[PDB]
Image (cartoon, rainbow over all chains, first blue to last red; front, side):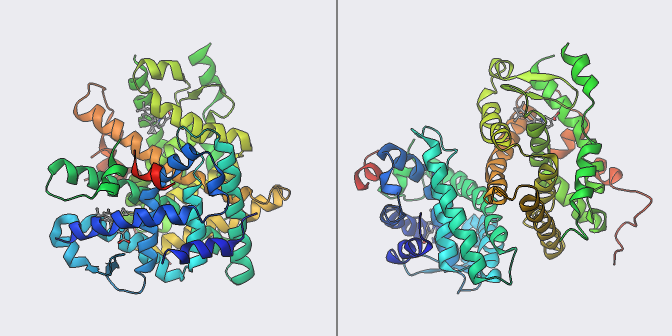
Amino acid sequence: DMPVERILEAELAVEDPVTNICQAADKQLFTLVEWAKRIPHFSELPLDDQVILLRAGWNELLIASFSHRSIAVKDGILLATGLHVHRNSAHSAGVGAIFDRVLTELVSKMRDMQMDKTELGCLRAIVLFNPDSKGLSNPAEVEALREKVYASLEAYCKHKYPEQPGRFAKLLLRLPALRSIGLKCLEHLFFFKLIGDTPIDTFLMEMLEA
Amino acid sequence: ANEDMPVERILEAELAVEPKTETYVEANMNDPVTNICQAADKQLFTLVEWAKRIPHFSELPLDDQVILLRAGWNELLIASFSHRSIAVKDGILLATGLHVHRNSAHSAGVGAIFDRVLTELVSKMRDMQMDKTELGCLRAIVLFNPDSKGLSNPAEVEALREKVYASLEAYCKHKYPEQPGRFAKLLLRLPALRSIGLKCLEHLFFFKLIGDTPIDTFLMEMLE
Amino acid sequence: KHKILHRLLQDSSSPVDLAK
Amino acid sequence: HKILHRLL
Ligand SMILES: Cc1cc2c(cc1C1(c3ccc(C(=O)O)cn3)CC1)C(C)(C)CCC2(C)C
Ligand SMILES: Cc1cc2c(cc1C1(c3ccc(C(=O)O)cn3)CC1)C(C)(C)CCC2(C)C
């Protein structure tokens, strides 16, 4: 059993444009570890398994945290450092194409359906409890845990949005979007450090580190 | 739920493009990469026929049918042969009827992604006993991807996609009422299918640009 | 400009883009 | 690594 509130408790308890974006992400990774330890049963896993899930997941877990929090601002992103990055700001830094992907595939669909925080935290716990991640000492423990989240998400969506029967499936069907933009964000960060013209701080660099 | 997007029509389209038993017979009783790419090219012609048979696809603007197929061919094509291989041990059945064992893929130096297909798609399709109606429904959702860059009416495509997964959900708890989580974990295979399609395109781009694998004309068009 | 896909997408029972 | 491992 993982109650959906404790998941809401976890989301709540932690709260050149590209240089500011990467700085915003570096300090959210410190945040990310403290959130995960708040997800029920996560700290029960083998520690190396905990490591694997976070290194496999961090990329999409951060995208989904700032996408949801940017539903208030229009045509822009609200960074964790309090700064707003408008679309034009990003376009004339040269990251326009992927910045728009986030705007049209995630924040707008988040806004347009009014996805709430509880639902956000469940999707983040689904992304965290990823059973196909290489090298887990027991992917079926993780899998059982992913089954507890999606069960606790369906029951939530129907008790509270009974007039929206397709809502729970609408949530799950943005996860392919989150994975596809997770990967292009990574292609970008490796290209940034290849070029060497973009400062990268020590926790973010470690996540890029092999 | 089933009235305008009926599971029975999507099953019909799936069955209509199933390969013949004979072909598996005549082929199992060139190099693997070239043999896979030749198969894939063949299925591309077939994928179109399959799309015209999906309720309402023919209604979308021609530009949007084009965008939807170019945006999802690879994922669609990988979905077909994964479920087609669900009773095969450590290998895939090609649309030409030829079997490719993972040891052939490893030999040819493409085993890692081949094993991803067997571990993340095929094997889980087996553990579940995913049927062809569910396969057709998951495929219909890939086709009806409203995120596809360039779409002229993404809202209509999202409507078509909502239609499918309302009918898919209804089928599942009708046929499998003792398995409540079954609808969810059917949908959770799509992120996996997304990464593998991406990885698969990386290989094809490599083969086209730097490689020597001959590429037939429709598959080559799909990589332009 | 995608000539294969275009040519394969035509048919008799449906119009190029007019739709209800 | 050292950071993520340490924090956990
Ligand atoms: C580092 C990083 C870089 C980028 C992005 C996301 C991040 C990440 C991140 C995490 C958290 C926050 C925040 O809350 O402020 C912001 N960003 C990795 C998640 C997107 C996808 C916006 C496209 C542009 C670039 C510059 C490539
Ligand atoms: C072209 C292609 C190449 C490859 C694969 C898949 C395809 C595709 C495909 C399509 C259709 C069929 C079929 O059913 O006949 C088979 N394959 C793109 C989908 C995988 C990932 C299996 C292994 C690695 C290589 C050899 C690079």
